[PDB]
Image (cartoon, rainbow, N blue to C red; front, side):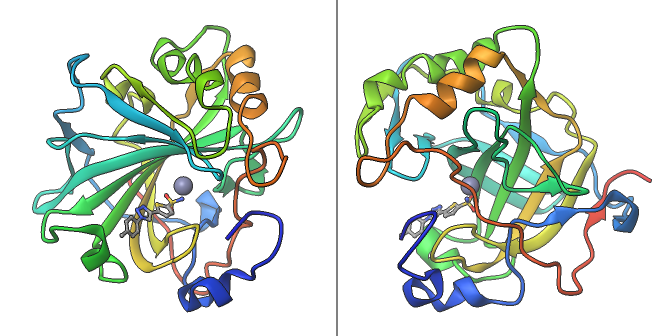
Length: 251
Ligand SMILES: Cc1ccc(-n2cc(-c3ccc(S(N)(=O)=O)s3)nn2)cc1
Ligand SMILES: [Zn+2]
């Protein structure tokens, strides 16, 4: 599969034609205030430098593989372990977030993909209710170099070629996300690439993460994908809610 053309994703995986897909357009006025949505809790995200982590250009994103021991809870008894994180972005003067807010597309987006502690492996969790959970935050331009992001972005030149990888020192993985874990939207949807399995709990933070202009340009201008193509605009079009109601943790 690829962004932009064939093969049609439903031929790759029938689940890509499900009724309840991601990403979606978030309309805050239509979101349901749900006070059971408590602040997200992360444990073990502050990593030592060794052992190193693998950072890979997989042709459709840059993905950092996360080690064992990163625990995340959506609430009491809703426990998960982090597997990996990756990014979605646009191109010179064009935004490339997956989720939108009232039609607004943000420059870029981070996804941190987690596996329910009830499952030993991802393949067993695919399509099961709440088997996977993704934390999603928008990346916007701020005035300062983001030092946590710089640790990844400074290494993209080493992995410019499709299918290449490098090792990076461990870092505070929570520093790639907003400091506000209280205010967010949450809904049930799908993986945004094949196999597009449903039952995924998506949490999209209110607060955004700030990268420099230079950093955003590095993200979108360094990596190459399938063929001789720049790896850019690597986002799926928004999918209709089709009757799902997005919940918000704040009125
Ligand atoms: C055997 C196996 C191993 C890994 C996967 N995984 C697929 C994925 C993902 C696809 C799309 C996303 S995303 N853009 O966050 O929704 S995460 N994450 N793990 C699926 C099957
Ligand atoms: Zn993603």
